[PDB]
Image (cartoon, grey):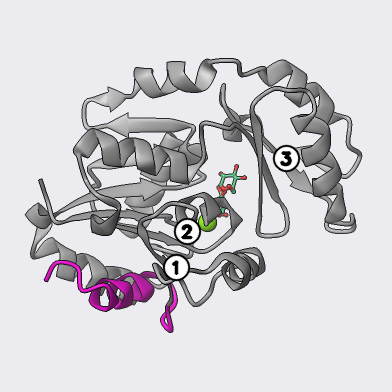
Amino acid sequence: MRQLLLISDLDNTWVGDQQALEHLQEYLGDRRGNFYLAYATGRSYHSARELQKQVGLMEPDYWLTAVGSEIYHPEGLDQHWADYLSEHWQRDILQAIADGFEALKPQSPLEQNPWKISYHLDPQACPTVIDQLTEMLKETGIPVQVIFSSGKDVDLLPQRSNKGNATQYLQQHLAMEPSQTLVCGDSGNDIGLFETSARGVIVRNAQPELLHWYDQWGDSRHYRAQSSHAGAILEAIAHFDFLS
Ligand SMILES: OC[C@H]1O[C@H](O[C@H]2[C@H](O)[C@@H](O)[C@@H](O)O[C@@H]2CO)[C@H](O)[C@@H](O)[C@@H]1O
Ligand SMILES: [Mg+2]
């Protein structure tokens, strides 16, 4: 029922340039009833909440955490989404395989959850290994997705997940159209957002992988901002003429 569904990652997209973050929240703060806000971050819910306290993030309507593997409504965790992602998902099997790659090191336990298996790629290892991993996991027949971002972060998620799928799920839930949705991202864990039919904005300080993606799949709904961080979101809002 609002004119805009604003979805954005936090670190180096919403957050990173304090001044830009502040004037972005000032502008939006003056028309808070005209849009739904959702943070689509790779961080866990607790880690996101912690960031909010550090930089003073404005309270969002929804939290799409751990790359969309968990969705938090004002009232709490979405159990429908969780059961949905649990169908045919085989965490143990996938983990056993991923654990077998010398080039991969598990991320801390606090970065893992039932629907997210994360690792770090060795800075000395050849990225092509990510391809070998993807192929090997897909062939198990388990609906799995491999998310590679910032040249080091690797997330194993159900196929039904990722920021984009969580976004579409949210859009349906709020009866918001893609034409009324704006996704903002900076890295490979945002590609899912741009595979969506919503309007999208790639921040100026975007990671190499996202830019490469844009070069190959960029469409007319995708905008490459001149501004970096929060500024790109204001720039995009003016570009797609949202909150007219
Ligand atoms: O999906 C990529 C990656 O995202 C999250 O990582 C954050 C990290 O917690 C931050 O402190 C900062 O460094 O930026 C990262 C990129 O957003 C997840 O926490 C991580 O597990 C995941 O792989
Ligand atoms: Mg990102």
Q: Can you identify the residue that label 3 sits on?
A: 119
- Is 160 situated left or right of 230 in this image? right
Residue plotted at (60% across, 30% down)? 112
Q: Are marks 2 and 1 in contact (CB under 8 Å)?
A: yes
Of tags 3 and 1, the one toward the viewer is 3
Q: Position of residue 72 (x, y in %)?
A: 33, 31
Q: Which residues are magenta?
A: 225-244
- Is residue 92 placed above or below 31 in the rendered structure? above
Residue plotted at (69% across, 22% down)? 142
Q: Can you identify the residue that label 2 sits on?
A: 11
Q: Position of residue 211 (x, y in %)?
A: 60, 71
- Is residue 182 placed above or below 23 in the rendered structure? above
Q: Earlier in the sequence, mark 3 or mark 2?
A: 2
Circle 2: is it few (<14), some (14-19), or many (20+) Cα within 10 Å? some
Q: In which quadrant of the rendered image does the C terminus lie?
A: bottom left
- Is 12 situated left or right of 99 in this image? left
Q: In which quadrant of the rendered image does the N terminus lie?
A: top left
Residue plotted at (44% across, 15% down)? 83
The span from disc 3 to disc 2 (Cα, nearest Å) is 19 Å
Identify the secondary structure beneath mark 1: loop
